[PDB]
Image (spheres, rainbow, N blue to C red):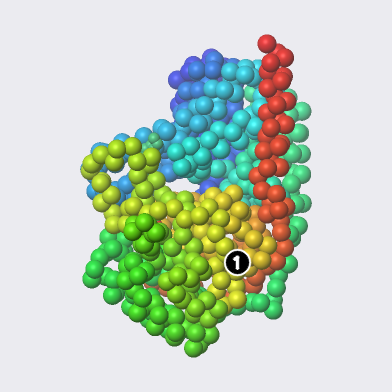
């Protein structure tokens, strides 16, 4: 009914911004509709056409609220099981988190329409990808960051997956924003010329998916076993369950010894402190060496500092053949990027008492080094990353080394819930394997335990929410991708070149 005048209304565009924003959630792992990434990003740039900077900022905020209000709505489950706050309060925090993350999308659309008001190819293909890179960086950097729901991860199986090993996932974000803008420009203004450019730019990286930046090593093939303990989150941290948790993991591991060269346990599989479990770990370490097996397990360690102080770390320790266990051994990985409000108090302003008050046990962890040596287990180099750290592509690459055999991640996705949460985390983990051309060994308490191939494919996987062991043969790969050699700087040079060119034209055109 008179769409020409109906679309001009600001309220109509705000309502459509929610719909197009929420459409981007369909691009990620539980749904895997990668065209929805383009459709969602076409609504972010078509609806902001011919708007005042404040009007465009509101449209960008509503688009972000639609994406984050439906994409990370699973945070309610994590908030529900943390602190035990009332239901209305938990709903408020999820809305507050979605509103906060939507500021960057609102900031992007406000600045984009402020400096490039005209609906031209410069705005959508040059200014938008460069400004999207900056605002997405800020979202993942400000206040410890939260770079969730980046559309580049939707192309893990799409035509643009070949661009990830060369320039990273953030380059797929750069190209998706460029292609979507040209399609939006070709649609709002009836003109096939930006349509052809978008299709050509989208089809150019397709042959890149057939390039193998790695070499398989069949001579070093091993049998890896990952024990999905499936320990309930409510009972995970209890004195009585400590014996049961150790018994469950040990009983599932004894048959694996000898048959499996590498055995992996999830994040914080041993819920007790590392110093409190020395007789158990020493006996376990000795038994593993007899049968020639190595165990890589997560554990909480409260290491006494020099100044008579305890620094609690979320650590991964290694036992068995190729890695003798000792409390002073450097063959360990301490988690560096702690989860905000779950492992530390942000900025520790006054630490005023509140309803949560760190209700969940072990909520005062410390930070490990940003760059740590790879774990060694039975002559195997593993680049470790605990849970959330696997989505930090640049941090994983910095810890990545040319002699790394596998990428290793252990997580406890019970906080993500029983919904799209664990899958979105799993999809971002698969990107690390694609970018670095290394097999990914992902072990979770009850989440998505899987082995990811060097090209991002799911080599093996087991169902969630069950007590099962994933035993499979995995082959290490060697060779450096262009992303592994360089990192994100070649994209930041491109962002600077596109940003500098676009800003110059903005200044030239008044
Ligand atoms: C203004 C900016 C912000 C706006 C408002 C934000 C509102 C909500 C924000 C944050 C709340 C989310 C907190 C979720 C906690 C998840 C962390 C966690 O418990 O992680 C576990 C997952 O693995 C660690 O493993 P575990 O062994 O199970 O440990 C048990 C814990 N000692």
Quarter of the picture containing the C terminus is: top right
Q: In this rendered view, identify the residue nearer to me: 144 or 434.
A: 144
- Pinpoint residue 276: horizontal percent, then vertical percent: 32, 71
Residue drawn where x is 50% and y is 17% of the image? 54
Residue drawn where x is 25% and y is 46% of the image? 357
Residue 23 visible, this orientation: no
- Pinpoint residue 77: horizontal percent, then vertical percent: 33, 49
Q: In this rendered view, identify the residue nearer to me: 210 or 333.
A: 333
Residue 291 visible, this orientation: yes
- Pinpoint residue 405: horizontal percent, then vertical percent: 63, 68
Q: Is residue 508 above or below residue 14?
A: above
Label 1: state its secondary structure: strand
Residue drawn where x is 29% and y is 41% of the image? 351
Q: Is residue 463 above or below residue 11?
A: below
Q: In this rendered view, identify the residue nearer to me: 441 or 490.
A: 490
The residue labelled by disc 1 is 406
- Pinpoint residue 389: horizontal percent, then vertical percent: 50, 53
Q: Is mark 1 within 8 Å of ligand 1?
A: no
Residue drawn where x is 24% and y is 68% of the image? 239
The crowd level at tag 1 (other Cα within 10 Å; few <14, some 14-19, many 20+) is many
The residue furthest top is 510
Q: Is residue 14 left or right of residue 355?
A: right
Q: Is residue 364 above or below residue 294?
A: above
């Amino acid at each position: 009914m008179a769409f020409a005048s109906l679309i001009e209304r600001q309220r109509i565009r705000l309502l459509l911004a929610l719909l197009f924003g929420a459409c981007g959630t369909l691009a990620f792992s539980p749904y895997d509709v990668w065209p929805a990434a383009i459709i969602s990003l076409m609504g972010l740039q078509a609806l902001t056409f011919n708007r005042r900077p404040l009007q465009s900022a509101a449209i960008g905020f509503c688009w972000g609220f639609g994406l984050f209000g439906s994409g990370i709505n699973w945070v309610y489950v994590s908030i529900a099981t943390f602190g035990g706050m009332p239901g209305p309060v938990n709903i408020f925090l999820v809305v507050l988190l979605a509103a906060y993350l939507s500021l960057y999308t609102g900031l992007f659309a406000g600045v984009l329409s402020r400096l490039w008001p005209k609906t031209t190819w410069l705005r959508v293909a040059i200014a938008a990808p460069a400004l999207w890179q900056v605002t997405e960086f800020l979202r993942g950097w400000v206040l410890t960051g939260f770079p969730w729901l980046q559309f580049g991860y939707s192309q893990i199986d799409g035509p643009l997956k070949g661009l990830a090993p060369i320039m990273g996932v953030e380059a797929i974000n750069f190209l998706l924003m460029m292609v979507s803008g040209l399609l939006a420009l070709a649609l709002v203004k009836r003109n096939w010329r930006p349509l052809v450019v978008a299709v050509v730019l989208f089809a150019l990286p397709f042959p890149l998916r057939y390039i193998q930046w790695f070499t398989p090593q069949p001579e070093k093939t091993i049998q890896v076993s990952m024990v999905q303990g499936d320990i309930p989150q409510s009972l995970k941290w209890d004195e009585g369950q400590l014996l049961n948790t150790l018994k469950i993991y040990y009983n599932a591991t004894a048959p694996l010894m000898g048959k499996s060269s590498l055995i992996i346990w999830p994040e914080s599989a041993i819920t007790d402190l590392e110093i409190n479990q020395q007789p158990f770990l020493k006996a376990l370490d000795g038994e593993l060496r007899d049968k020639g097996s190595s165990l890589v397990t997560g554990i909480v360690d409260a290491r006494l500092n020099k100044q008579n102080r305890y620094d609690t770390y979320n650590t991964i320790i290694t036992l068995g053949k190729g890695a003798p266990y000792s409390y002073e051994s450097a063959d360990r990985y301490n988690k560096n990027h702690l989860v905000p409000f779950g492992e530390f108090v942000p900025l520790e302003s006054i630490l005023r008492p509140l309803a949560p008050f760190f209700d969940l046990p072990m909520s005062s962890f410390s930070r490990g080094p940003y760059i740590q040596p790879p774990l060694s287990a039975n002559g195997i180099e593993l680049t470790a990353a605990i849970c959330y750290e696997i989505i930090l592509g640049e941090q994983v690459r910095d810890n990545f080394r040319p002699d790394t055999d596998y990428l290793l991640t252990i997580s406890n996705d019970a906080w993500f819930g029983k919904s799209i949460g664990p899958w979105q985390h799993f999809q971002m983990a698969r990107m690390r394997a694609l970018e670095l051309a290394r097999p990914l060994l992902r072990s979770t308490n009850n989440g998505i335990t899987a082995v990811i191939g060097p090209q991002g494919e799911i080599q093996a996987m087991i169902p969630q929410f069950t007590r099962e062991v994933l035993t499979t043969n995995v082959t290490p790969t060697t060779g450096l991708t262009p992303y592994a050699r360089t990192g994100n700087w070649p994209l930041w040079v491109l962002t600077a070149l596109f940003g500098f060119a676009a800003v110059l034209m903005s200044l030239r055109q008044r």
